[PDB]
Amino acid sequence: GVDRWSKDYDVCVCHSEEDLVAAQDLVSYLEGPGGAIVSELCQALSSSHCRVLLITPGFLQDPWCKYQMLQALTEEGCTIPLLSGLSRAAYPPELRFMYYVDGRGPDGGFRQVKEAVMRYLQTLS
Amino acid sequence: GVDRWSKDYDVCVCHSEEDLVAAQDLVSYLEGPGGAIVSELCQALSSSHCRVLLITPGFLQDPWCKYQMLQALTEEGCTIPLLSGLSRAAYPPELRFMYYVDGRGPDGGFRQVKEAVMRYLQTLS
């Protein structure tokens, strides 16, 4: 129902400082009549339809990352946790009850992440 | 701005199964022209102005509790984390950036929890 053009970006990737390269790859992977997916790294003032949480060891050890995760789940919305480089036993327990993409999927999860984003965009006017 | 009478309870206490007694005490403590504070234990269909998270070891070891915490912070609202029976080093990292009540305060934190609730009620019509 929400207008696709009401935000400038379709998706941004929220990531810890030590996962920059990986985040960049995902951005690139997402960039490749509803047009291409407009993508960027999440920044303090980023406004996008979808937000990918690149949940890694680095992400888990930064309290601020955890806080950002909380802010992403306050909205109907589009938050896509991607679990990368972690034992499932160490996944955030909340995710036992939530949607997420396992990094052990195709293209390190990227594929499914992309699909999720596309799904969400198809619900936009 | 929101009408005080728009919800039936002013506060409910969200707690793990092994903290029932403690939760009850807090409820009792909260019960003791804006009238008495109407209080109960949180249940699946509880609707209250304020929600206290009784964050304990028991709470931390139950993934569902964690999930409830997340649901409490999706709204302006009134969510009061109370940290009880835990080393601060083991507090949920999110709380580094959020308001909470330390159980090492007066009356095991109860006092301050109560104050918070009262503050919130004073902002209601």
Image (spheres, coloured by chain):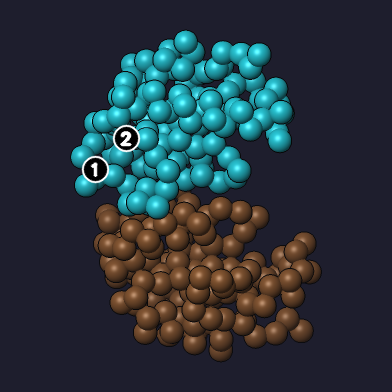
Chain colours: A brown, B cyan
Quadrant containing the C terminus of chain B is top right
- Residue at 31 percent across and 63 percent down: it is A62
In the displayed structure, would residue A61 be above or below residue B33? Answer: below
In the displayed structure, would residue A106 be above or below residue B103? Answer: below
Q: Element type at marker 2?
A: strand
Residue A83 appearing in the image: no
Q: Amino acid at mark 2?
A: Asp
Q: Is residue A119 left or right of residue B24?
A: right
- Residue at 65 percent across and 85 percent down: it is A36
The answer to which image quadrant residue B88 occupies is top left
Q: Is residue A125 left or right of residue B120?
A: right
Residue A92 appearing in the image: yes
Marking on residue B102: 2
**Front-most of A49 and A34?**
A49
Give the chain letter at badge 1: B
Residue carrying label 1: B88
Residue B26 on image: x %, y %: 40, 19
Q: Given contact means CB atoms under 8 Å apart, are the residues at marks 1 and 2 in contact?
A: yes
Quadrant containing the N terminus of chain B is top right
Q: Element type at marker 1?
A: helix
User: Tag 2 or tag 1, which sits nearer the N-term?
Assistant: 1
Q: Amino acid at mark 1?
A: Arg
**Front-most of A105 and B55?**
B55
Spatial distance from mark 1 to mark 2, Cα to Cα?
9 Å
Are labels 1 and 2 assigned to the same chain?
Answer: yes
